[PDB]
Image: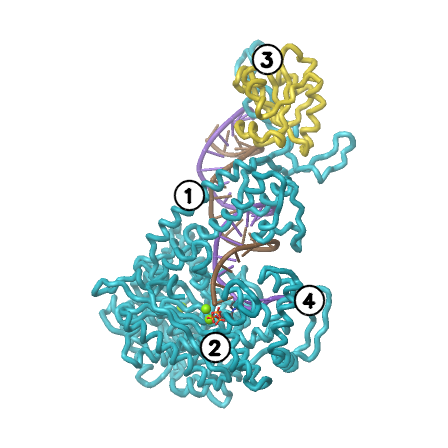
Chain colours: A cyan, B yellow, C purple, D brown
DNA sequence: TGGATGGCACTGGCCGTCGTTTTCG
DNA sequence: CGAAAACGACGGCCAGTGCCAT
């Protein structure tokens, strides 16, 4: 086994030069450094480890180092380099599995200070190395006199870079050892730093293998990217911007601008007494200014000529209140609230900090006498929605148009194990939060994401999209877990017609989507009021629905009961939270990992969300593997390409319809496989849609 | 009272087309300095009667005029002399500083 | 006692860098 | 010429609110 890391001139997409690398060999207990000209020797060594059926350990190597080495080996040495999956270990992947309850800085992309809770020490250091190095470089660049530009720190190799390169490895080695010492994932009778690759995977908790496969597959997906119709979203931005302009025109006309105190340093004091009056806006007593300026002539100095008048403005001693002129901003809930109250609106919902709630829900119900202002409300709601679309599609810091790459695709990031439950997280941008096809402008947004927007590299023909989603996943997960209580009744009934549509009819809801929001809100202990809000009624309609549905599957209580007994010893209830005494603070996931439980009231959700997340994770894995054992190639230069994974859904680009039909059928076989793999008490299924884009495929 | 209480709609002809000097006071009820210079203005209205006109404009009740003058602080005293701003001083000057402000501009 | 798990926009307060303007020593 | 002073466009940080999706 060996621990390694490299230093190059840029992130994966733009990297074109290997600066250096380091390898620690457990078989020799020694570090070896490689410089620019040692590149070939570096690759040899790594390949030597593979030849011995060994293991290579990288921290974030799966997403960066490995694919990068492949890219540089070709560009720089015109050599084919491809470390097999089974030979690679990633401590960032391991760290995220074992410390799932914790956050990390996604290798320096996020700010530690903005992250809640603690951060594992070794990983924190690794994620800050690029920044600490920049500081150390930007410093030596001042001691010598030169100035600093962009990110020159990475343009050329230097021994300062080499030193960090070495420390990364010594630090990655410690992290590796710390992680391996956890007896829950690695049996203690085995030295995992002295075993062949097949042994490392087979002797460790199934979870270790799954996570490394997911990460390997997902890094590939990132590289693939999601074919994006830049032009279309570009024209939509033009449409939305015009509409925002018109509403702003009407709104600023309906609600006039106004002034406000601003910049007041000193405090206003009573003239009579001297009593400071905090209530009054802060003031500013200038000490520079007068009627005329100081004399400039012999005449002025003598009074024979009026001194130059002072065009200053202020007059030393004369206190004034500085103010700013503000123009009505529809995006400011503070403004909306101010204007609406001045029109007779009386809020009936405030926040923890006493601020009157101003969301669409309350706006929807606001009523004022003035017809014009009353109508302005409908314009404010539109403006907010329009803005939301612009924010996400063009203007925000993570807007689609700011992330489309040269290859006409958006390479969103994925943290395969970013959520406690085992779900993944998505960002830059979050391709898992794209407006639903049925929401305002949903179709246009969704349609801009699609295989059709990618043209085959050889024929120039548009690719086809294959969309697959697990059917009623978490509800089938519930059925599995309560099977020991209802002997599989629910697991059987859930299969009589679509479950959500059926529930929709029973609850008399308007859409299937609304049945999904209801049932899950219900299953996870939403109060009567919230249930009302979800279905558009009140607390009574909520209590009704709770009984009506809990009455049907009373076993849900039994399950809830057992989860409580297994986790909690006893619990109280103070003034700012619940004080709990735990028997065990975690749940054993389907692949054996520990799944931290944050709260007793969320235990069931932790159980079912985790089961769904791990089922789906094993699923996308088995699916790609079946496609591959079928002779299909993963890549735009092949037959299919994973474009996105949205929890229990996958969107795959295909070279031809035929391939898309096979992908769809295969995903289905895969789902059933997984269900059999963990002896699930509820049959698992998936629904597949062939089409041009995301709007048609989900 | 001999002070003109303006409105956005009346401002133009009461001020910009008045013939003779006119001192406009852009104020707000929530400003301490404003409530201070007020009394002085009432007096300055009689003392300079015939020499100029003293008018007040409440920027809350009349938000459209002030913006045209980039008012950044209050109370603002804009001295008009035929549609044009003659002199401009901001702050709750004293009865003395004000008279010295006018005289030098009248 | 509670829907859950996440990303992320946008305002507004705090704070400090920084290029521009004015009357004065 | 620089210093003291009144400024505002400006970016990094952060808390509070609320919308995106599964
Ligand atoms: N408001 C929601 C919506 C969904 N989910 C969870 C549980 C199901 C999982 C995936 O969402 P869907 O794909 O909508 O789940 P589904 O019930 O399998 O939907 P379908 O059968 O329609 O595919 O996410 C949730 O916790 N809260
Ligand atoms: Mg690295
Ligand atoms: Mg689903
Ligand atoms: Mg889904």
Q: Residue drawn at (42%, 71%), measured in percent from left and top?
A: A469
Q: Earlier in the sequence, mark 1 or mark 4?
A: 1
Residue beneath label 1, please? A242
Q: Is residue A99 left or right of residue A44?
A: right
- The residue marked by circle 2 belongs to what chain? A
| Nearer mark to the viewer, of 3 and 1 | 1
Circles 2 and 4, Cβ within 8 Å, touching? The answer is no
Tag shown at residue A614: 2
Label pair 3/4, CB-CB below 8 angstroms: no
Instruction: Give the residue pinned by disc 3.
Output: B106
Residue A429 is at least partly visible in this image: yes
Disc 1 to disc 2, how far (Cα)? 45 Å
SS of the residue under disc 3: loop
Q: Is residue B32 above or below residue A520?
A: above
Q: Residues within 10 Å of mark 2 (few under 14, many from 20)?
A: many
Residue at which label 4 appears: A577
Which of pointers 1 and 2 lies earlier in the amino acid sequence?
A: 1
| Image mark count | 4
- Which chain letter matches label 1? A
Q: Nearer the viewer, mark 1 or mark 4?
A: 1
Which of the two labelled residues, at mark 2 and mark 4, occupies the earlier sequence position? Answer: 4
């Amino acid at each position: 086994m060996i621990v390694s890391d490299i230093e190059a001139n840029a992130l994966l997409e733009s990297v074109t030069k290997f600066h250096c690398g380091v390898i620690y060999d457990y078989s020799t207990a020694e570090y070896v450094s490689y410089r620019p000209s040692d590149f070939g020797a570096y690759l040899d060594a790594l390949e030597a480890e593979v030849a011995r059926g060994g293991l290579i350990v990288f921290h974030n190597g799966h997403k960066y180092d490995v694919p990068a080495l492949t890219k540089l080996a070709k560009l720089q040495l015109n050599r084919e380099f491809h470390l097999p999956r089974e030979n690679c270990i990633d401590t960032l992947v391991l760290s995220r599995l074992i410390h799932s309850n914790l956050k990390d800085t996604d290798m320096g992309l996020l700010r530690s200070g903005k992250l809640p809770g603690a951060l594992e020490a070794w990983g924190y250091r690794l994620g800050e190395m690029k920044g600490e190095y920049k500081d150390d470089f930007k410093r030596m660049l001042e001691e010598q006199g030169e100035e600093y530009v962009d990110g020159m720190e990475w343009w050329n190799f230097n021994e300062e870079m080499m030193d960090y390169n070495v420390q990364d490895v010594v630090v990655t080695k410690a992290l590796l050892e710390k992680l391996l010492s956890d007896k829950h994932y690695f049996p203690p009778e085995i030295d995992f730093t002295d075993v062949g690759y097949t042994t490392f995977w087979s002797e460790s908790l199934e979870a270790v293998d799954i996570e490394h496969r997911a990460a390997w597959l997902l890094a590939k997906q990132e590289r693939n990217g999601f074919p994006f119709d830049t032009k279309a979203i570009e024209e939509l931005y033009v449409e939305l911007a015009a509409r925002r302009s018109e509403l702003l025109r009407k709104l600023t006309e309906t609600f006039g601008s106004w002034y406000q105190p601003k910049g007041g340093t000193e405090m206003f004091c009573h003239p009579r007494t001297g009593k400071p009056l905090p209530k009054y806006p802060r003031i500013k007593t200038p000490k520079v200014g007068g009627i005329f300026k100081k004399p400039k002539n012999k005449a002025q100095r003598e009074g024979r000529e009026p001194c130059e008048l002072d065009t200053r403005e202020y007059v030393a001693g004369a206190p004034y209140t500085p103010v700013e002129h503000v123009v009505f901003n529809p995006s400011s809930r503070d403004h909306i609230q101010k204007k609406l109250q001045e029109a007779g609106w009386v809020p009936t919902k405030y926040t923890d900090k006493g601020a009157p709630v101003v969301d669409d829900e309350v706006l929807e119900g606001v009523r004022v006498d003035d017809p014009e202002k009353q109508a302005a409300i409908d314009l404010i709601k539109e403006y907010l929605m329009i803005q939301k679309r612009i924010g996400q599609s063009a203007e925000g810091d993570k807007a689609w148009l700011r992330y489309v790459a040269e290859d006409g695709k958006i390479h969103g990031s994925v943290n395969p194990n970013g959520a406690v439950t085992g779900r993944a997280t998505h960002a830059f941008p979050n391709l898992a939060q794209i407006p639903g096809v049925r929401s305002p402008y949903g179709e246009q947004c969704r349609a801009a994401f699609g295989a059709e927007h990618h043209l085959d590299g050889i024929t120039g023909k548009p690719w086809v999209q294959a969309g697959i989603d697990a059917s009623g996943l978490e509800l089938r997960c519930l059925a599995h877990f309560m099977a020991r209580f209802d002997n599989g009744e629910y697991a059987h009934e859930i299969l009589n017609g679509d479950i959500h549509t059926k529930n929709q009819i029973a609850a008399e809801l308007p859409t299937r989507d609304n049945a999904k929001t209801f049932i899950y809100g219900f299953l996870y202990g939403a109060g009567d009021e919230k249930i009302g809000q979800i279905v558009g009624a009140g607390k009574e309609r909520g209590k009704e629905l709770k009984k009506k549905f809990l009455e049907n599957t009373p076993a849900i209580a039994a399950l809830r009961e057992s989860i409580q007994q297994t986790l909690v010893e006893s619990s109280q209830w103070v003034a700012g939270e619940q004080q709990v005494k735990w028997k065990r603070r975690w749940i054993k996931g389907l692949d054996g990992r520990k799944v931290h439980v944050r709260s007793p009231h969320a235990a069931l959700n932790t159980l079912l969300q985790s089961a769904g997340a791990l089922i789906c994770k094993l699923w996308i894995i088995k699916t790609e593997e079946m496609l591959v054992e079928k002779g299909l190639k993963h890549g735009w230069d092949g037959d299919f390409a994973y474009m996105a994974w949205v929890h229990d859904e996958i969107q795959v680009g295909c070279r031809t319809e035929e391939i898309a039909q096979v992908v769809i059928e295969t995903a289905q076989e895969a789902m059933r496989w997984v269900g059999d793999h963990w002896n699930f008490r509820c049959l698992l299924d998936t629904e597949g849609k062939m089409g041009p884009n995301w709007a048609i495929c989900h | 009272d001999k002070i003109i209480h303006l409105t956005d709609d009346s401002f133009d002809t009461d001020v910009l087309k008045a013939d003779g000097a006119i001192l406009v006071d852009f104020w707000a009820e929530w400003c301490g300095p404003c409530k201070m210079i007020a009394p002085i203005l009432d007096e300055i209205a009689d003392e300079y009667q015939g020499k100029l006109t003293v008018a007040k404009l409440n920027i809350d009740q009349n938000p459209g005029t002030a913006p045209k003058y980039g008012i950044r602080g209050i109370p603002t005293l804009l001295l008009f002399k035929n549609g044009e701003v003659a002199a401009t001083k901001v702050g709750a000057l004293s009865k003395g500083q004000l008279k010295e402000f006018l005289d030098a501009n009248l």
